[PDB]
């Protein structure tokens, strides 16, 4: 008959774990808090068999914008998600805007995930807003010169 | 809000409600409840069918000096106003309305589309507003106005209104209200639920 | 560059989803799009349905510590209440077995 | 399928004829990644060039094939009615190139639901295609309705 | 359960150690500040297993230039690093310009 | 960048920011300690059944 | 919570540094004074973060 | 590695990280004692038959 | 190494089973492959089902 009490204890433990995780990630740029959603599990009888966690819902409200200053740092306002790719080509999304250039001069975050975007091609290069998104690179190669054709 | 754009609870059951039908969409309460959905479907444009311009006029204005009318010359008219209307494709037509005082309490209003570069400048009165003993508009408050044809879009014809316009000892001629029922295409920006249960997409 | 001329190397793309709550977090402050969240709609900042980008700044978490502490207190009390229920059932079963 | 929105106020490009290298020669460029019989990715570039109000010539090119012929003939013609709704020319059969001997794919590209009105600028509403590349089993699940799905 | 709170305490302690290192190094020619960057540890379940320290990022902002009157003292404005060699031939890089 | 002779580049540590961050960090640490205390009470309650 | 006061303190410190720099250049030929410009940081909520 | 004169290498024991582990291990020990008590009651109810 | 060059010595292999539950536990936090679990599939980390 512990059908209800055990489920209630498990739900309370899940909620407490969610609260503790929210407390722990308090200083994680790009973190969104979570809240457990509970539902009852009446089954045929009217005795109220127990409770269950229907899921965990994020809170996608914009956090405070703090001017750390480092140029690469980019904060995102309102809706939107930064798009990254791992070494195996999978696509991921993140609100954390702490970026750095790696040794191959590829814009990566702290975990090494390559930031993606519309690349530029041509001479002079133009933003290929149509071109499928590609990892952004910042080459240090010397820039060639254009012969004067219009003045 | 799920992937199919329906309002569902945590367990996935779809919220139901009275749907909106017609243009402009309004809640038809005679129908059975249906699941509420929020599509991104771009909103199409509405060419204008009714426009309104409420203006107050000055009694002491002298008649224009430089006859005849020219849309180029400022001294050729008493007042000039601009109303933005929209055609079948949502292109902006800037109707300039020109006020020239003809006699006492009598004001000829001209209409010219400035968005169409090939449109000829009006030379004949579009309408003659008549104001009674004290501002009270007397006649001529409504006129049919036809747009120009721009970039292949259907020209939008509409009824332009001067109702409740007044002409008294006001300091100068300034526009009080301009309204029109047309709009340009727009994409979904936000959605909200009002306290009366209506789901409204902005 | 040093020749009094600049080049454009790329434009950061932004993603918007029909269902924000459907994104499954993979850790390392990173989300992955799944069936419930739908396909990602791509665009640029400041155009369409995307907010602009603030330079030289970072977005902090939206976790308020006061609310978290109060919710922790309430959840602890609920957990202890459920434990009391468990103890009640334990005493009932003990009473029946001792018969 | 490629649903796009076009602006009615765009001037006709000056640089006739259309050139892929010349950015001034076309109004809008988009990309769709299709897959051939073997699984190679073909980045088909679709170019929209306005000719006369309510008329748009559409050109196609293969950006993954180094031996693809330069497009000299308009692939199709989109004609929008006076209300901005597409009337004719929304479907065209297009064949890609051959990469490393792989058989070229012939597919129907459809511009259905594309509309030309007074938007902000040329924006691609949606792009989709029914081809894919080889895939390895990653996970399996049993859904709510009992269907077993492998991701 | 315990793991989430333990990880949170460890991350807070790491942040406080970074702050202590920065504050103890407030008077150090050529020193750059540090900042701890944290990341969560979701794995399969939606419960949010916890947080981890992704790394410590230096802040390479050009500091204030202070004169001293010594001829062997030189500071690097903008970007650039002094290249140094130890006894074993290993190379090193430093922004501090105190030489003797 | 250019080199300036007769001077040194001082540290970029601003003390006020460090103090405020220290205050925030300590409070976070206390919140996590409270979380541990709560879970400890939970385990005590379950054990003492 | 803390972020609002942190932003306020940082703005005040920036203003103080600007004033101190201007005073330090009281005798500096061709120098033009500087002044910090402040703006609120409303984001979604009506609280007006910082 | 290098040798530094006039300096000593202190211990690497962090007190905070230890106290927390002490709490966790206390809870594990109490849980095991609870299991022992449960088996004791099992043997009791079997014996008293 | 000390010559400012790194050298690889090997790569850790990962094994996945068709039936994880069928593995026979041998103790010492160690599992052994059996007929119920099936033949182990070998591979590298971060690829395929690893």
Image (tube, coloured by chain):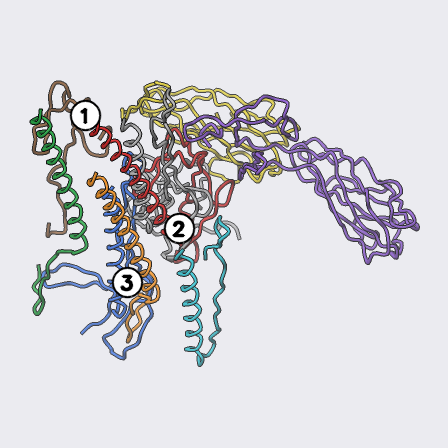
Chain colours: B purple, C red, D yellow, E blue, F orange, G cyan, H green, I brown
- Residue at 32% across / 71% down in the picture? E65
Q: Which residue is mark 3?
A: E32
Q: Could you classify mark 2 by the number of other residues whose Cα lies within 10 Å: few (under 14), some (14-19), or many (20 or more)?
A: many
- Camera-side residue of D150 and C12: D150
Foreground disc of the pair 3, 1: 1
Label 2 residue SS? strand
| Figure quadrant of the C terminus of chain I | top left
Give the label on residue C99, or none: 1
The chain ID associated with circle 1 is C
The percent coordinates of residue D41 (x first, y second) are 36, 28
- The chain containing the residue under callout 2 comes to C
- Residue labelled with disc 2: C59
Marks 1 and 2, Cα distance to the nearest angstrom? Answer: 64 Å
Same-subunit check for callouts 3 and 2: no
Q: Chain of mark 3?
A: E
As drawn, is H5 to the left or to the right of D112? Answer: left
Tag 1 near tag 2, CB within 8 Å? no
Q: Provide residue B31's location: percent of width, then percent of height.
A: 61, 22
CB under 8 Å between callouts 3 and 1? no
Q: Which class describes the residues within 10 Å of circle 3: few (<14), some (14-19), or many (20+)?
A: many
Determine which quarter of the picture holds residue C92.
top left
Label 3 secondary element = loop
Residue farthest along the front direction in this orientation: C99
Residue I30 in view: yes
SS state under label 1: loop
Instruction: Name the residue at 43% across, 24% down.
Output: D129
Q: Residue furthest bottom?
A: G27
**Residue F45: horizontal and vertical position, in percent?**
23, 42
């Amino acid at each position: 008959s512990f059908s209800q009490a055990v489920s209630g204890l498990n739900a309370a433990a899940t909620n407490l774990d969610v609260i503790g995780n929210n407390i722990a990630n308090s200083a994680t740029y790009g973190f969104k808090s979570g809240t457990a959603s509970f539902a009852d599990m009446f089954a045929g009888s009217k005795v109220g068999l127990g409770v269950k966690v229907a899921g965990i819902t994020q809170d996608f409200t914009d956090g405070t914008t703090t001017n750390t200053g480092r140029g690469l740092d980019v904060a995102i306002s309102q809706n939107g998600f930064f798009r990254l790719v791992d070494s195996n080509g999978s696509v991921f999304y993140s609100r954390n805007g702490q970026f750095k250039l790696d040794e191959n001069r590829n814009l990566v975050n702290m975990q090494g995930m390559q930031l993606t975007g519309y690349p530029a091609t041509g001479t002079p290069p133009t933003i290929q807003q149509g071109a499928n998104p590609a990892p952004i690179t910042i080459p240090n190669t010397l820039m060639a010169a254009k012969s004067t054709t219009t003045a | 809000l799920d992937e199919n754009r329906n309002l569902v609870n945590m367990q996935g059951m779809q919220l139901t409600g009275y749907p909106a039908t017609g243009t402009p969409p309004t809640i038809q309460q005679g129908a059975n409840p249906a699941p509420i959905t929020i599509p991104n479907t771009l909103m199409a444009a509405k060419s204008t069918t009714t426009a309104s311009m409420q203006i107050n006029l000055n009694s002491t204005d002298p008649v224009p000096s430089k006859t005849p009318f020219s849309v180029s010359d400022a001294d050729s008219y008493n007042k000039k106003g601009t109303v933005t209307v929209y055609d079948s494709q949502g292109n902006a037509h800037d109707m300039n309305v020109y006020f020239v005082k003809t006699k006492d309490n009598e004001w000829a209003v001209y209409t010219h589309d400035s968005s169409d570069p090939a449109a000829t400048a009006p030379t004949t009165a579009s309408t003659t507003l008549k104001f009674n003993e004290n501002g009270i508009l007397e006649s001529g408050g409504t006129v049919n106005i036809t747009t120009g044809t721009i970039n292949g879009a259907t020209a939008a014809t509409f009824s332009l209104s001067f109702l409740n316009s007044m002409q008294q000892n006001t300091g100068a001629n300034n526009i009080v209200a301009t309204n029109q029922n047309g709009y340009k295409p727009g994409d979904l920006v936000s959605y909200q639920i009002n306290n009366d249960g209506t789901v409204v997409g902005n | 560059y040093s020749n009094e001329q600049e080049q454009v190397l790329g434009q950061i793309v932004l993603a918007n989803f029909a269902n924000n709550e459907g994104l499954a977090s993979q850790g390392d402050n990173v989300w992955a799009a799944t069936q419930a969240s739908g396909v990602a709609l791509l665009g640029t900042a400041g155009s369409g349905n995307f907010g602009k980008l603030t330079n030289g700044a970072l977005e902090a978490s939206n976790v308020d510590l006061s609310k978290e502490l109060v919710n922790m207190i309430v959840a602890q009390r609920n957990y202890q209440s459920n434990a009391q229920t468990i103890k009640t059932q334990d005493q009932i079963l003990n009473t029946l077995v001792n018969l």
